[PDB]
Every structure is written in C-alpha cells, then in structure tokens.
Amino acid sequence: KNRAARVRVSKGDKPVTYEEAHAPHYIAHRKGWLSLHTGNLDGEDHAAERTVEDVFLRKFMLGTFPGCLADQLVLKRRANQLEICALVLRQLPPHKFYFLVGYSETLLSHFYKCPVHLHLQTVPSKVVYKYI
Amino acid sequence: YYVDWKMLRDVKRRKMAYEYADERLRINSLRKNTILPKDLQEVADEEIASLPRDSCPVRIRNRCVMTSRPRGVKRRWRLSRIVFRHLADHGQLSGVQRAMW
Amino acid sequence: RRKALPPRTEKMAVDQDWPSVYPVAAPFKPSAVPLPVRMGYPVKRGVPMAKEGNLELLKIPNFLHLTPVAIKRHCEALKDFCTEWPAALDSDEKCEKHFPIEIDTADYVSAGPSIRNPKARVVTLRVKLSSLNLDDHAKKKLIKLVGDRYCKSTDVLTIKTDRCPLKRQNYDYAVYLLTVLYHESWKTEEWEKKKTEADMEE
Amino acid sequence: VDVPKDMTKPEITISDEPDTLYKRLSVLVKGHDKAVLDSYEYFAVLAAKELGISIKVHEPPRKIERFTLLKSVHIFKKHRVQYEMRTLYRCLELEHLTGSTADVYLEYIQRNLPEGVAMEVTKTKLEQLPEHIRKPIW
Amino acid sequence: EEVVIPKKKTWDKVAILQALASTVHRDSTAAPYVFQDDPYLIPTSSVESHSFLLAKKSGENAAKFIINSYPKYFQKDIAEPHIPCLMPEYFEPQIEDVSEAALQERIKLRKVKASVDMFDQLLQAGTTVSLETTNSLLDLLCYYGNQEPSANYNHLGVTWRTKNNAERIFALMPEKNAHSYCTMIRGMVKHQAPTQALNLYTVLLNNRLRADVYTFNSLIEATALVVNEKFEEKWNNILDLLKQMVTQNVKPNLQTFNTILKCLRRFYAFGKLPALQTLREMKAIGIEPSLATYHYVIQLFYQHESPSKGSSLIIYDIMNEVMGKRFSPRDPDDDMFFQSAMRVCSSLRDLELAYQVHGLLNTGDNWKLIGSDHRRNFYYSKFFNLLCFMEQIDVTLKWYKDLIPSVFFPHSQTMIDLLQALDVANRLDMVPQIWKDSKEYGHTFRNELKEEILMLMARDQHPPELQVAFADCAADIKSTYESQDARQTAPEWPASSLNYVAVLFLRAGRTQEAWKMLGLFRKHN
Amino acid sequence: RKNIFKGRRLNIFEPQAVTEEAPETEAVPSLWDIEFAKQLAAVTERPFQNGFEEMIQWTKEGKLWEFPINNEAGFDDDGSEFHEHI
Ligand SMILES: [Mg+2]
Ligand SMILES: [Mg+2]
C-alpha cells in the first residue's frame, strides 16, 4: 500500500486541511505546487541551488514561528526577489509578529543576498476541509 | 557538521582538486601531445604523479547534499532518490508531478 | 484578548478604482479582494471552500494588478518613452534594400540571485550577398572560402561567434570576420591560377 | 476629491545618437501551466495593441520530460514510480520595433512576469554595411 | 535617401517606474503600506502605530546586530551582479598594527577611544602626524564631546567641559589654520558654551585668518546667548558680525538667515521689522528661502493678539509667493513649516488659506516634508477641525473618509468637532455610523465621546424609524460600559449616561427594554 | 497692503552675481558637511508609501535588477576588446 504523504483514516475525529487531504498523485490535478520557480523548466539551469534554499525556508519559518504556523509555506520567486506567503494562527501579540517580520526580512536578505518579501495572513485556527 | 564523515572527506577532496586544477592541466597538456619529445613526456609523468593523491578529478564522488547516499542520486537536483520523492510528493518542487500517460 | 477587525471589503466603494488598491504584484489577500471566489475540489455533498484561509487561491499568480482598466492607464503613460518607426520602411523588401545586415542577439531572464547565462554571448550575423560588391571571381572565392556558412538557395551568409565572453566583443568579432573575408576575396594571389578542372563549380 | 496635483516627474533626454532599428523581435515565454500563459498572452497583446506594434502570437509545440525512480528504499525493483515535468511554450513576435520602443516594452513585460514562467528574447537588429565595406577599399 | 533614422530617447533606469507610479494614487480604505494588510495586524489607533512600527524597526537592528557579530556566517556570495549593500560590515579595526594608515581607519569607523589611544601611541613613537589628520581627529572628538556615538549595543546645563581633550590637543597643535579655529568655535557654540567661542574668535582676528560661512552662523547665535542685553545692543552686535563677514568676503548660506529668525522669536514685538529686512536681503543675495525660513517668519508675527492685522498681511503675501512651487529639502527644520502653517490657519479660521497650504503639500514630493508622526497627526488635527464648520457637511464627509483612517487616527476632541458639524447641519442620521467608526479608531472607551453621542441622540424626539437606529447604537454603547477595560481599577457609569439610554429605549417600540432600565436608577442611585 | 519682500533691506552684503567657479569637491570632506547631508536626507526620507516607491529605492540601491535585463550587467571583463582574447 502506498504511504507517501498521506494521512490514514481513523474514525471521523481527526481534522485534515486541504493540503493533507489529497494524495500525492493529485498534484497538478487538484492542488498546485507549494513553490514555483524557473529552476525546474526544460532548458533552464540553476535548479539545485533553488531546492536547497527552499528546504531551509521550510525549516526556518517553522522554527521562527513555533506553534503559530498553520500549514506549509508558499514560495514565489520573481526576478531576484523572494516572496514568502504564510498562514499564522492568532497566538503571539501583534508586537511580536512585526518583530519577527522585521527580523526575518533582514536576516534572509543578507544571507541569500537577495530581497525578501514576507506576507502574512492570519486565521483564527487551522482550516478544516474534511472529517471533524 | 556534515551529515557523515564520508561527506567531510569529499569536501576536502573537492577543495584540493580546485587548487591544483590549473597546474595539472598545464602538465597534462604535455603528456597528451605526441609532437613533444618522448624524453620530456617521461619527465612530465613523474611530476603529474608526484602531486597529492586527493588532487584528482576522478576521485570526486557525487553524493546527495542531504543524506549523502553514494548512489541513486539525480545529477540535476543533487538529491538522493528517497529525498527527491519526499520533496516531490508533498508538492514542494515546482513543475514536478506524477507521470500519467 | 486582541480581536479581529472587519475586512476592508465592507468599506470598499462600489465605483472605486481597482488599480489604486494593487499598484504592484502582490499575493491574493482575502480581506483586500471584494470578489467572493471559491476554489478547490468540493465535498461529495457540499460547495468549494471560501476565499478566507484557502491556500489554493494563494498559490496562483494573480493578475489583479494587470486589469484591462489598469493596462490602458499604464500603457498610455508609457507612450511618451517611444519613437515612431519610419514610414518608408513599410515593406520588408525595402528593409533589405536600405539595410542589408541583420544581427541576432539574445537576452535571458530567470528567477534567481544571478543573471549570468553563458548562452547569452552568442551573436548571429546574416548578410545577403546580392547586396554586396563582389565580382564574378571574388564571389566564387568567398563561397569556397567560408565553407558551409553560405546557403546556395537563399544566398544568405551566416556567421556565428561564441569565443568572446561578451556580446559586444562577439559583435565586434563578428563584423571583423565579415570585413576580412571581403577584403580577401579580391586578392587574386599567384597560386590561384593552379586551378584543377575537377574543382570548377561550373 | 483631494488628489495630489501633478505628481508626475519623468525626464526623457533626446540625444543626437540615431536610434537602433530592430527588424523583428521574438519573445518566447515558457511555463508549466497553460492558464498563466493564456492570461499573460492577453496582457501582452493588449499592451502591444495600444502601443501600435501589430504583433502575431503562435503556440510552439510542447515537450514532456520523464524519468523513473525506484519505489521502495530496499529491493523491490519490479515496482516503479514515474514523474513528469511539463514545459508549455508560447511565442509572441514583434515586427518593426524601434530601439526606444523596444526598451520600454521589454521592461514593462519583464517586470510583470509571473513567478512560474520565464522568457527569452531574440532581437534581429538591422544596420547598414560596415565602414570598410561601404567605403571602397579595393 | 527616403529614410530618416529617428533620434533615440535616453532616460534613467528608475524613471520608467515613476511614470507608472503617477497613474496610481493613494487608496482611501487601505492601511499604510509599511504595516501588514492582515486585519489582525492592521493598527487600530495612533498609539498602535508607534508601537507597531518601532517594533519592526527594532527587528532590523536586531538582525543587523547578528550579522555584524558573526561576519563569517554571511561571507558567502551568490549575488550577480554584486550587491555591496547586503554584505556584512566591520567595526573592529581590520589592521591591528600601530601605524598612521591604521589610525585613519579607526577615525572613519566612528571610534573615539581607539583613535585617541592610538594617537597617543603614535606621538610617543616619534612618527610625524599630518595636520589634516589631527584636525580630522579633533572634529570627531569635538562633535561627541570626547564620547562614543549612539550604538545599538556594546538637556539643561552646559555639556561642554573645561577639562576636555579638544582644548588639550588644540594647544598641542604646532601649526593652526583657519579651519582649526572654525571647527573649534562651532563645537563650543553647539555645546552651549559660547563664552569660549567668542574669546577664541578674538584670537582668530588677531591671527588675520578669515572665517568660513559656518563660523559666522554660530557667532550670531553665540552673541545673543552670552549676555542678556537689550534688543538694541544685541542688534548692534548682530550688524557688527555682518560687517566683519563682508570684510573677509564670506557669503552666508540659507541656514545663516534661518537661525537669526528663530532667535528673533524671543523678541515677539521688537523683532517684527528687522525680520522683514533679513528676508528681503535673502532675495537680493540670491538664496531662495526654504519652508523653514517662512516657518520662523509666520510664528514671529503670530502671537496671542486679537486683531492679528500684521499676521494676516504676513501669511497672505507668503502664500501667493509659494503658490505653484515645488520645494526641495534645504534646511533641517523644513519639516516644521507645514505644522506651523496650519497653526496660523486655526486662529484665522480661514478655510481658503488652509486649502492653499494643503494644496502646496500635495504638489510633487512636498508631502514628505510634513514632519514626524505626531507632527502629522497635529497638522491634520487643526486642518480637519477647520473642515467641519467652514464648509458644507457634504464635502466634510468626503474629507473625513479620505483623511481617516488612511492618513491619521482622529482624536477624542476631533470626534466632538465632527458631531458639532452634524448637529449644525441638521443631520443626525449618521450618528450610528460615527459610533461604529469611533470604536474602530481607538475611541471604543472614551468617556468624553460617549456622553456627547448619548446626549445628542436623546436630546429631542425622533420618528420611530430614526429612533430605532439610535436605540441600536445605544445598545452597543451599553455593551461597551459592561465590558470596560477599566473594570480592573474602577468601573464607573455616569449619571447622564444611564438617563439618556433609558429614555432612548422608549420611543423605538422597545417598551419591554424600558422596564429593565427602571431598576438601574435605584441601583446606581 | 505692502508686500513683505518690498522695503528696506541690509545693504552690507553686495548682491553676488555668480557662485564659486570651481567648488572644492575633490578634497578632504569636512565632517559637518557630511553631517548636514545625513540630517537633510533623514528628514526627507519617509517610510515607503506604495509598492512602486519601494521598487525605485531598491533599484537605486542595487537590490533589484536594472530592467530590461542584460546578462552581462556588472561584468565588463576588465574593459578588454576581442583582440586580447583572440
Ligand atoms: Mg548518521
Ligand atoms: Mg566516479
């Protein structure tokens, strides 16, 4: 039985978001790609450097916002600027969010030597698509 | 820390090759040409072999940058086949989808 | 604790100008978009999810900043930075008559911290031989000298340069090849009289 | 009602250098999703028509890249999981475009490029004969 | 030939965006672009704006502290073309050897303790030191008073000290030029020590060394502050410095005249005529007055005088002169003109005068010279109050929507002014929407605003359609009293507040709700 | 009824027709002049009010590319013609 990126059925008491409720074979059929960039085109180079930077942001954003992160990030790369879209729960005071926003924008910009955009959308809780 | 001691040795091997990449190229040019006298070529073989062992392009090994699996690594993404599926099945790689035809 | 303010969609005017809300490319903000849009595969008996808290509406590259109303306003302001194409060069035939040399160059744009693409240094120079001043003997020598770069059907000569790192160096090298080939086709050297009857093109 | 009066301040210095003439400009956008390219074509055509460029749009044939990887982490080589990368093409040709008009059109096009696509520009610059060729030198 | 090649157009690489930026204007309902567009993060009051923005500003400083603390973690570069504005910086001296070249690095890196210690070692070494380097060392020490500048992490009285290193090194100088005296005088005047600066100028005259433009700028301020003589004696000294300035052929700058007008503000009566003479001199010299120059002129003529005939003449002539002009920054106090200009219009109560001031602000990039956040709030505070009664309510509401909350958050007193305009305009139908907007604008629990709204709604009888709307607003107001944030210290229900709410729930077909209000009077006495 | 710009002025300073012919910009920069530049610019600069305003500031600072994109921007190869490479 296939087990790649799936949540198993357990009665009807475990909530599942839209991203986790679809099997990996539904990619490009029901859900899009969490990250979009030129590296994986047909005749374009510089694909490995984009991948490793993508993984670091998955680990940095998750640790920068402990517990308050809703689901996976969305990474958009236009020109030389990097846009990060996140869904964050209403956990920290708004003072701390702006502190982390300023801390993240400056630190990543001086590490990858490229401008970074960090846009946040706040939700009361995790959005539930099935079960519950 | 690199993920394994094997990965650490590869970094030193790549660094050593880069330093002696130009010197080896100049010496190897003499060997690979038959118009120079054979006496000079024999001296060239002694000098090129006197260089440190780690400064060899062939000894460079391509591993995965995440788990350092010596084989089963795609060259384009520099990732092992297990790690590549882990990122691709979650939709974290652009333009990568399950093949259906 | 802190509460959630109502979205600005309620305060949005009926006839307000949209492009002022989105001047540049920005991600889809559910509070900033008055349009009620639902996407995602629905439940067996249900409706697709709403626009708030939906990642599917966030992955898509929106075109809210390129509305047709904004496009006309954006383009009209840019009309100052333009100069008209000459009217006499209407037919493509006259373009060849007045300009016999065309040069092909390429620029590449990709998402990343770097722009250096090694494939952008290529320069392609194409010249129609019928517009030059080659003689009967000089033209035959030029074809035999340039090799396969000349097409016998379209009578076009193509020169490709890749050794120079930059496009300007290749462009200066490409034109250098064209002029040195013309000045050499007119030099009837002494050994040229040693022609073989099997080497004659006619 | 209250608006910033005359908030426009660009300068266009007309020099004495003759402008560069391009015989034909080709733009080839490549991406993974057709919908983005369909909308991007509409944006480019609408802007091009307003500037008066008389462009033509054609769709080059697509190509599909496939590769196969093992399924499990140990043995079981009779079961494979395949993957596919789809790159969709769209070409927009520009004819009889001046150098000054080419610069603004490209930068306006490039700045609004979606994050999931890229493009290549092939400019066919035209010019007269070189000085040595034009000036009679044997 | 029948073909003419048109001439190319050359433009800067950033002017293309500015052409598009002209088409797009400010958005009425949009929060400031600096803050996030998310409603949970959108500021709700002017108090939040300072807290939110400074928190983000501290984030940049916090991150840059990490970058500079560990330079080795950011040396990797993958930026093409190279961006020198993202590479980590260095503050420690890159050269640890004792040499003149390494000494210059410490001076340029805003290091005071390292420079003075290394300079002493250089002197003990016997190696010669350039006079310009010595003057450069003095300038760094004089400006900060032999102290360190303000760093991320390691008013009354004369800040200048007699036992200071600046005087010690100045005496030790073998050769002293005009610049050495000029920079010493400016520091003394800056640090509220003009007695020493004037004495040094006398020695400077004995040295037959001409003073630069900036020296006379400090001397004029120094002379007035040293003694407390009358205006006539001060003015004679002021004219004396100008005559000496002509002898040395020194042309005063814009700031030379601005500081004179600011100091003349103390003489609110005797300095009116001399102020005009200096202003006419500026036009003759050729130095165009900036916004700050007119800022001191209007305030000097504007006092607590009922006639204000002279002030009216001052402002009217200026506004015609400044009409249709775009101003570039030319004075550190240019940002205080717009706030000061609105103060004059507040007393004169001239709406037409305010529009000329506001129209000037919206021309070109002149809006960037409004001032700080509190200056911007104060500038719009007086301006919006004038928009209430001086104009029809129909246009007043349009200005209310555009300016608030996009530009500034209204004050409690400003809300009272809006209510007065509605009452005068015989329009009470917008009261429920005003209260709803009041809660959004940080005025949820303002006792002053609550009383005014309740009194106006229940002042007179209304048709049942309008009465229900007032009752719905009153019910929300009643809920606010129940959930006051001051209940931790002391919850207070005003006597008037209870009365009007009880009366309000009578004529809206809410007789049942009125019964519950009867028992509140006895409970609250 | 009298304009404030018309009347008696101070005649001590003669009206200067022209400024300095050759400014000394290529010399040791005085500290106070640099401080004046910081003060004048800091008051002038304001937090970004629109997306376009953020783009132009980055473009001048070098954060963003100079559109239209040329792949050889910032790399002139020591300003050498093709002869040094051929
Ligand atoms: Mg291990
Ligand atoms: Mg091998």
Image (cartoon, coloured by chain):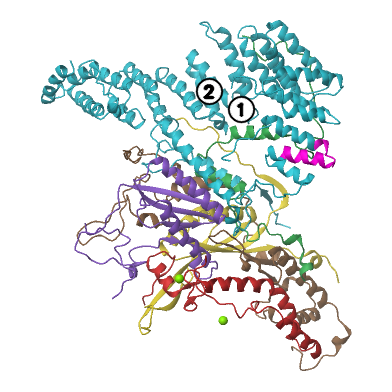
Chain colours: A purple, B red, C brown, D yellow, E cyan, F green
Residue appearing at x 17%, y 20% in the figure: E502
Chain letter for mark 1, please: E
Q: Is residue A79 visible?
A: yes
Residue appearing at x 41%, y 64% in the figure: B92
Q: Which image quadrant for residue E365?
A: top right
* Quarter of the C terminus of chain B within the rendering: bottom left
- What amino acid is found at the position of numbered circle 2 in the picture? Gln
Mark 1, secondary structure of its residue: loop
Farthest right residue?
C190
Q: Is residue B67 left or right of residue C100?
A: left
The spot of residue E250 in percent (x, y) is 80, 23
Secondary structure predominantly adopted by residues drawn in magenta = helix
Residue on which disc 1 sits? E325
Q: Which image quadrant for residue F4?
A: top right
Residue on which disc 2 sits? E339
> Is tag 1's residue or tag 2's residue first in the polypeptide sequence?
1
Chain part drawn in magenta: E115-132
